[PDB]
Image (cartoon, rainbow, N blue to C red):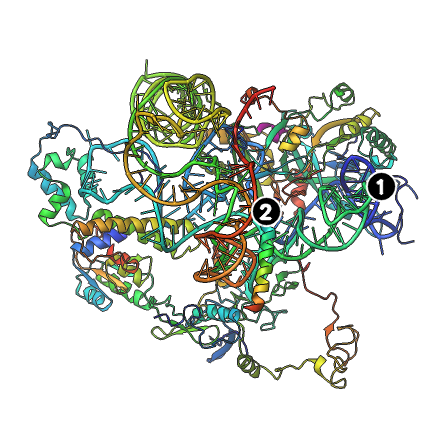
Amino acid sequence: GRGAPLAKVVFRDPYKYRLREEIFIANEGVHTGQFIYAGKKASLNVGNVLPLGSVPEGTIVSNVEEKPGDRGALARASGNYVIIIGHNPDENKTRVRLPSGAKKVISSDARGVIGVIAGGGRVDKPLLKAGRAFHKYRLKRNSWPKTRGVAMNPVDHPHGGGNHQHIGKASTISRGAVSGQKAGLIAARRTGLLRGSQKT
Amino acid sequence: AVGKNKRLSKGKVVDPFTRKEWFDIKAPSTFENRNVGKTLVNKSTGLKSASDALKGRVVEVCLADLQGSEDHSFRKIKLRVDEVQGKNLLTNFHGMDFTTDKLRSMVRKWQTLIEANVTVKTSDDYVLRIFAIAFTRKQANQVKRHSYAQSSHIRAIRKVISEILTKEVQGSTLAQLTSKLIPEVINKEIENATKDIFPLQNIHVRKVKLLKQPKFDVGALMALHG
Amino acid sequence: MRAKWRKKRTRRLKRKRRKVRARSK
Amino acid sequence: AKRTKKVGITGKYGVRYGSSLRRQVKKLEIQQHARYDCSFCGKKTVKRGAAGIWTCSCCKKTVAGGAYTVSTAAAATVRSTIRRLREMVEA
Amino acid sequence: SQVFGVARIYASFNDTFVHVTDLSGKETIARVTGGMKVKADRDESSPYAAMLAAQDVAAKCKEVGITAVHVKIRATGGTRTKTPGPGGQAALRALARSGLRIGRIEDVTPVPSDSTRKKGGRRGRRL
Amino acid sequence: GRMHSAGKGISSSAIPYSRNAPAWFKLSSESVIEQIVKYARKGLTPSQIGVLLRDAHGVTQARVITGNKIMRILKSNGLAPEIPEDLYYLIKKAVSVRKHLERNRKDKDAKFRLILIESRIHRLARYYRTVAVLPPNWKYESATASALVN
Amino acid sequence: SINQKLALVIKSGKYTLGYKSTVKSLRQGKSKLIIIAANTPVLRKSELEYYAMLSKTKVYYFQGGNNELGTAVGKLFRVGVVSILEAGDSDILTTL
Amino acid sequence: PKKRASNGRNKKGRGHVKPVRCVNCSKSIPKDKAIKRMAIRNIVEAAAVRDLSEASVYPEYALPKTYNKLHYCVSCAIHARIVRVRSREDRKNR
RNA sequence: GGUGAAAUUCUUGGAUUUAUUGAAGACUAACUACUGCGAAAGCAUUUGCCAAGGACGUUUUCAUUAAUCAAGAACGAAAGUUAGGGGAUCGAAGAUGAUCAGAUACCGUCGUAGUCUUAACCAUAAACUAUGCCGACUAGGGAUCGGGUGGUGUUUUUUUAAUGACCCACUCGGCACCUUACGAGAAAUCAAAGUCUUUGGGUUCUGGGGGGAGUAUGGUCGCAAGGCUGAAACUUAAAGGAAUU
């Protein structure tokens, strides 16, 4: 159900004589038998989990925590990474560019894994046949095949009904719409083909 | 176009210089005649006050006025206001810039322009990007009117220029660096070190612009303005 | 006519002939 | 003997799915099924396992990488930038 | 014994700007321009209108308290003209002859280090 | 000239008219011959043997001092390389560009130079095969080229 | 160069190839210099350094892989470590 | 027929140079082909220095001069009378 | 704000302008030249790495391994195409402002594709020096680029050694240039476009009046746009080149 391979990194419990097994998302360049140094005073190496408050600017990180003590919030998909932009000494906060392209400000005690999540470029090959899509979605959830609402009856969908296949009303649905009318574009600021820069 | 505007206010008196107070500027002790000038600022109110609105300011002056002499006219010193003391704003060194008249004057044709820059941190943690310029010269008795270089002496002098600037900046503070650029001793050091590669002329340092400022340290400021 | 405009005209005319060609062959 | 002159590996799909899609899946499948070599041993034995996993048969060391490539160009650039930053900061 | 300021005489075509500024640069005094004195929309940058515009900039500054200013005459800059406007030099003479002493004239026109592109196309402004 | 370039510069060695020279030379013919094989025993190519004997010893050229040439002496005493020296360096240069072109693929200038070197190697190999120096079935194999240079 | 020096040694002096043969040469003390590629396992490299330090020999590192070491030696296969039994007509023992 | 030995302008042995833009009509022209005139004119107009000197703080000594290099296209240079046509004998003159 | 003049458009919601910064992409002025390199296209910030190349110096080596080229192969401006990233200026289309009898043209303001880069295609140009490549000879003059040689030459560090940078003389390869016209050309002009009716150094390609026509068809390459090869029927007595008045 996930396109990113997993790596089983085991540590040593400092308080009890017992081996702890941890599940980490494998990063590119990480191999079996590799020693991973997770903590604050580690080195800037691929696979290490140093917090964002002790790394230079421009650092590429993965598995970024939104808040301290989160154990992985952002950049958990294959081929994605988070870019460090800057840090504020007073009121320690790190500024991050997310894979979406949205600026974020998080705490300096948020641990992140150095590197790029493995399995990058996964969505570059057409599924070609319906069998591949069926197998991919079976391991994820019951969301395939999807039936168009314009080909439905008026009772089974707001967009259905009529002697033809047309929506009838505007596809754009306001944000303050109750459950039932939200069938289409939700709070669509703009429509049509995205030509030119997105002004992000 | 006093009578061509159609829509003047789409929505539908007291002179503003009565609520403004003069503030006299002062300069580091590196420059002899402190005597910077005066600037306007809104009167100290309970909402925004005058110190906060005057705290961030960079005033540009000329080195000839600061030092009194006239051989520093082509160099203008930029001073940044960062703290006040009751109607006398105090500044600090922020950068140095060669005037457009001088820079375009030494830049002639039939000569080689040697340029270099260095990113160097001082003792007081002032990350500085220092620029330098140099032009090849026609030596005496020479009849060839191009006086060009072979692009290998340029690299050699560029390396010597970079290491000279690094040596004289790493191991000194911002105040010492300011007291070093005014006598133009760095130019003498370069012309002593790159005279065995190519004659060169018009050895100068272009910009000493600032990049990073350390902790405020109001203690150093009080030593600067004695 | 200019060489560019004459060549463009005959190229558009060739495109039209080939479009007519594709209908039968 | 060049059984297929242009179709190449994806002759299994036949005449279906479109020439452009067949070409794209051929371009990616060539690298997916290509044989690579261990950086820990040098023998050309690295082969693709699951998505993002590259395991071998001689050295048995498994590497995490791209879906169809043992080393993504973006990953290589990121590693180079990380090494440069580490060298700058630790000097 | 003399408070100082900055002229910032922006000289271009179809318009001219004289905007007296204090030493620091934040304060603004007498931003009058040459387009609010002429009623032709073609003499806004003419030397005859710059003198009238600068005749008021030297009086408001005197009333405010400024007696002398520095001069930084500039052009449109960027990648358009790089040359001073027709009336920029006339504006400097107007406030100099109005009793306002000047000094340290500077050229601060923005010269680009080969940035962006210049409007007009590869075949020029064919007129 | 310049088989694979547009240059036309002339620069070569101008040997003297004296076929019996340099008169002031005093060492014996056998003394220089054992010096040639001693330098050849330590992997020096015939060009370097002549270069070293010309600037360090009093041997102007090994043709008038001896009765034969350097390569001729090497073959007679059994220190002749399997492949010609000029071909050996050409193949050595060829694998250098191939090594350069296996990492930086976007270098079209190296690709053009590599083709020129490979064409030059093939032309030289044709003459050597014709003159009965290399095996008649000898060929330049890109994969085996690195092994040939040893 | 190091490649030319190794080729000269292979041509003239006595050489042995492989890891077990290198260990045997170190044990018998017939080895002077050993060259280990930068691609060998770290455990094997460390044991080779231990044997070299016990036998008072010299250690050199080939900045490549087993393929590159074999190519420099003059062999088609992969060489992880080469032990230099006799210098021969070369100078790799005295210099570098 | 051929007019000049240097066909466009001053280009023998290069084949291609980075073009420049005219300052008047924004026409794209080769850097060699462009006709360049250097302006050394003073920052002030003709005369009027004596008016400036009386209202000049410090002992004057400023007298700045603006320096600019202007590139003109063939059409604009002829139209602006900067470059004028000549006879065939005068064409060869440099 | 802009134009010859205007207008669209932006301006009490502060336009334009000024001062302190930040972000994004593009680009490599001035130095920049009858200057350099590269097979051509082409290449201008600094530093590091990788391999490559011309010239020069050489009493080093091989030895005729060479020159030109059907077929065939590599590179090949811009524009265009496929799939991502990027997308600030300019800007095929398009939307408006005008001018004009008409203006979906020139001018003004916006603006998509594109302009940048990654991987794969496109094989075109006034891709021109409209002048194929190799070799030999032939009127003089100066400047300049790279290397080399000589002159107690000048300057430079420690006045004075070296080296470096300059002056003079010479040499090899260059980008080229000035004056003449033995000689050539229809002339314009040419140090080759000369050494061709005193016709022969080696080799490749192309053209046989102007249109039809680089069109039609047949092959071939390409995702397409298009590239390569490539007619005939029919029509005309003229087109075309250089100069003179």
Chain identifier of the residue bearing label 2 in the image: C
Q: Quadrant of the N terminus of chain F?
A: top left
Residue D25 visible in image:
yes
Residue B141 vertical placement versus B192 (above, below): above
Residue I45 vertical placement versus I193 (above, below): below
Q: Nearer the viewer, residue I149 or A33?
A: I149
* Total labels drawn: 2
Chain identifier of the residue bearing label 1 in the image: B
- What residue is shown with label 2? C4
Magenta region: which residues?
A: B101-106
Q: Quadrant of the C terminus of chain F?
A: bottom left
Q: Nearer the viewer, residue B1 or E28?
A: B1
- What residue is shown with label 1? B20
> Of helix, strand and loop, which one carries label 2?
helix
Query: What whole-number distance in Å separates the C-alpha atoms at marks 1 and 2?
Result: 69 Å
* Kind of residue at disc 1: Lys
Residue A96 horizontal/vertical position (percent): 62, 62
> Of helix, strand and loop, which one carries label 1?
loop
Residue at x-position 89% and y-position 46%: B6
Q: Nearer the viewer, residue A33 or I8?
A: I8
Circles 1 and 2 in contact, beta carbons < 8 Å: no
Residue B49 visible in image:
no
* Kind of residue at disc 2: Lys
